[PDB]
Image 1 (cartoon, each protein chain N blue to C red):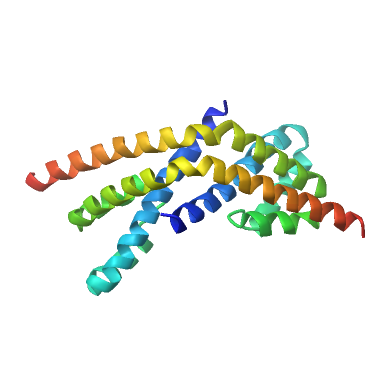
Image 2: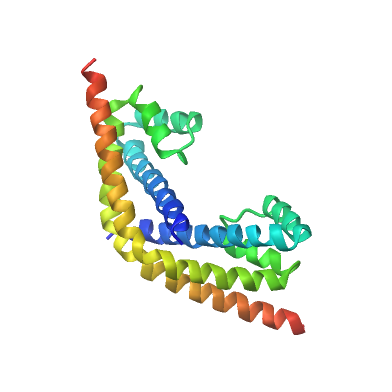
Length: 109
Length: 110
């Protein structure tokens, strides 16, 4: 329950980073298509799932954008983290409900 | 309130906890019933856990007992872990942010 929470937090760290790049990209696509297109070719070269390696690699190519990510991911984290436990737990119960109903019906079908 | 982003993160989290459930259950089975653990291995190559609903549903065709074990374990895990994540991820991002910032500004320093 602690190894699990560590692994989960790390995954969320990567995930929110990803989500930051996504948002920045929606904006670049409108604002600097050159850069937006650049970003795509970059994330193909580099696996966003590795948050830090992704950033460290990008430090070598577009320092301004790396800093913008760090800021945006943190904004997102503060906008979003707090509502997560309610939303996930409630979603799991609902999904657990549906899957149980489904398979208990399926057993007798 | 970033709604689209909370919705997509929650969903991701839902699946990730399912994954984490499958991971424990997999460890138990590897000791208890090796045959079944092998099965759960390649089942997982045939079906991506990131789409957890589709995964559990496809599993229903093959091992309804396990589907039920997954549902229970994942909910337990959720109860154990969710509470602690907002402080944990925020404090991690801040740290990581500081390190990246400090490392980038020192790269310019050279």
